Image (cartoon, rainbow, N blue to C red):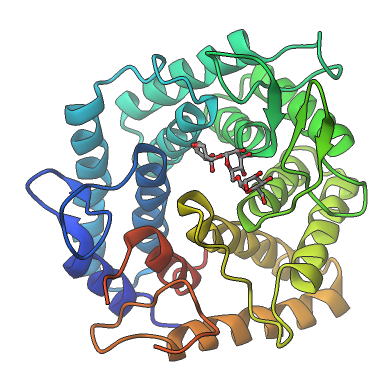
Length: 335
Ligand SMILES: *[C@]1(OC[C@@H]2[C@@H](O)[C@H](O)[C@H](O)[C@H]3O[C@@H]23)O[C@H](CO[C@H]2O[C@H](CO)[C@@H](O)[C@H](O)[C@@H]2O)[C@@H](O)[C@H](O)[C@@H]1O
C-alpha cells in the first residue's frame, strides 16, 4: 500500500532536523531513547527501500546518514560503555543494514566493532550452555531481546563480509535461543535468569527478532527447519498476541514494549517475502497475508487528521509518541 504519506507525516511530526534525532513525543521536550532511535533508523531505511517516489527516496537517503550523525553527536562513536548489551546490538544491527544499503565503510566498522564487543565479551557457556548476557555491568539473565537481535546482526555481517565466523556466531546464538528461550512450538520466552530459570512471557518484539533471525538463517543455509521455526513463531503470534478480533495487542504502558509492533511488523514482512518467492507453507501464506492486511487496514483506520497512528490500533481515536506511532508507518513500508 502507500507508505509514503505515513513516513512524511511521521517526519513532519517527530523529526528534529537541528539535533538530527526524532523527538520522543509531540510535546518536543526530549529526543527519543537511544535504543529506540536505532529502530526508527531502521524504519527510515525500510521506507527508503519501499518508496517509488524519487523525491522522498532522496530525502530518506540523506536521513539515513543524519540519524547516525545525530546519535554520534550526543552519545559518541563508541557505545561499548552502555551497560545494556541489547542497546549496543540494536545499533550494531542498524549499522550493518546501513552498510548493506549504502556501502559506506563507516557503517561496517560501527557494526563489526560493536557486534564483536558484545559477542566476544558477553557470550558465555558457564550459565545455561550458551547465550549472551543482557547487561555487561552484571550477569544475572540472558534475554531474547539481546540474543535474537545478535543472531540477526551476525547474519547481516555474514551477508556483507562472507566471513564464516559470522554465520557460525548466528547459528550458535540461534540454536541456543531456540533451545533455552523457546518452548519448541513457536513461543519465545523473555529471558532465562540464574536463580529462577526461564521467564516464559511472550512479546511482539521477541517473536519478531526470533522470526527475523530464523528467516535469515534459512536464507544463509537453505535448511527448511529454520523456516519452519519462523512459521511456528508467526502462527504463535497471530493466535496469541492479538485481541478477540485478531488485531495485534497494545503492549503499553511499558515504554519499551509500546512500540514493539514496529519490530514485529518489520520481521513479519521478511517472512511474507520469503514465503512469496519460495512456495513454502502455501495455506499459511494465504491466511498470513489476510491477517497482515487486516491489521494494516485497522491501523490505517486509526489515523488522526495529521496521518499519525498511535499504537492502540483497536481503540478509539492528545500527545502522540514516536515509538508507539512508528508501528503503523513500518506496517505500511513492508520489505
Ligand atoms: C527489560 O528490557 C527493556 C529494554 C529492551 O526492551 C530493549 O531491548 C533495550 O535495548 C534495553 O533497554 C532494555 O524489559 C523488557 C520488558 O519487560 C517487561 O515485560 C516483560 C514481558 O512481558 C516481562 O517479562 C518483564 O517482567 C517486564 O514486565 C523485557 O522484554 C526485557 O527482557 C528486559 O527485562
